[PDB]
Length: 187
Length: 187
Ligand SMILES: Nc1ncnc2c1ncn2[C@@H]1O[C@H](COP(=O)(O)OP(=O)(O)OC[C@H]2O[C@H](O)[C@H](O)[C@@H]2O)[C@@H](O)[C@H]1O
Ligand SMILES: Nc1ncnc2c1ncn2[C@@H]1O[C@H](COP(=O)(O)OP(=O)(O)OC[C@H]2O[C@H](O)[C@H](O)[C@@H]2O)[C@@H](O)[C@H]1O
Ligand SMILES: [Gd+3]
Ligand SMILES: [Gd+3]
Image (cartoon, rainbow over the protein chains, first blue to last red):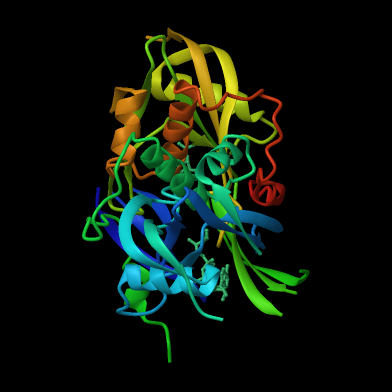
């Protein structure tokens, strides 16, 4: 395949719409910052989840703490750690890579890195705590549909059941977005 | 929350970009057809997966057979069944709902229904067959990143391990997209 020509159709707050001419057909791409989410598992196998309104669906969805990689030059896990604190007031001693997911492969370059945070300390001074198994059943029951949450919950469930292991922070993030950030549309 | 006003910024082949004024801030939404995917498990616990090029990432990703709900008035599972046949030349006697996922909750209304198809017959006249456990490990190892694939693979893995059950075809698909189709931008 080959990109013949590409044209910017729109630049917004968190993404830009671009149209390319490929190998020869049209291919519209939503350039995204990319994001990070966190599965913060405590000493008893519970993780915190937030109930957030999503205008796209016109309703609140249960999700993992998460934020966009909108801070230029900021390392992903630093962004992640920041969100875990701001989102659920937790700090973690151990940070590992749990699962990366390409959210909308058909039309956007967004990719999300989900970290597994352990060794939690409540710091600072809607969300709910769920036993990992309870969370896994909510997924398989349709009560958790956010794609990042689904991946993170079922991944940590596979880990907690001894089926798989978390990974090193230096694990390559193959599809981490760069296009939108490269635009630097900020005065 | 409340949508003050909404403006169409772009209408493309598979999606439209719309900007709303919410409750008061800007909220850009990518209206999508929605899609369906299939986890076709054979009698030995294997499922077929396709290796497809995704321009968004500039590379091929391992995925579950899937297609957009771009056929007006066509029932999702009929679309699904059609794709399973066209994509991997398989027909299934049993169709159930496995997992629904909201792909990019932050900027698009797309939602994808993943069905579990069983009782397979090879019909007609790149893809590969994977034991469900092999597929689950590929996910946790980063070799499967497509979000729909991640959800489907780990969901059927939870099913095959006896942790959860498939669901009836009449299960409500809460976030099934309707906006883009409603536009009917076809002469
Ligand atoms: N469609 C949009 N249009 C304009 N602004 C938006 C839009 N969507 C979100 N924003 C905004 O960006 C800011 C949200 O930042 P974060 O809290 O860092 O991230 P978040 O929206 O929760 O997304 C993290 C991740 O989860 C979602 O599943 C989303 O798809 C993304 O990958 C919001 O306060 C608001 O300015
Ligand atoms: N960004 C795009 N711009 C223009 N046309 C596109 C674009 N992306 C895909 N298409 C096209 O739509 C048709 C593909 O249809 P399907 O095979 O029905 O579906 P598919 O693209 O594989 O997507 C199914 C699902 O998987 C992906 O993860 C995608 O995010 C979606 O939910 C392609 O042949 C081509 O016309
Ligand atoms: Gd935030
Ligand atoms: Gd097709």
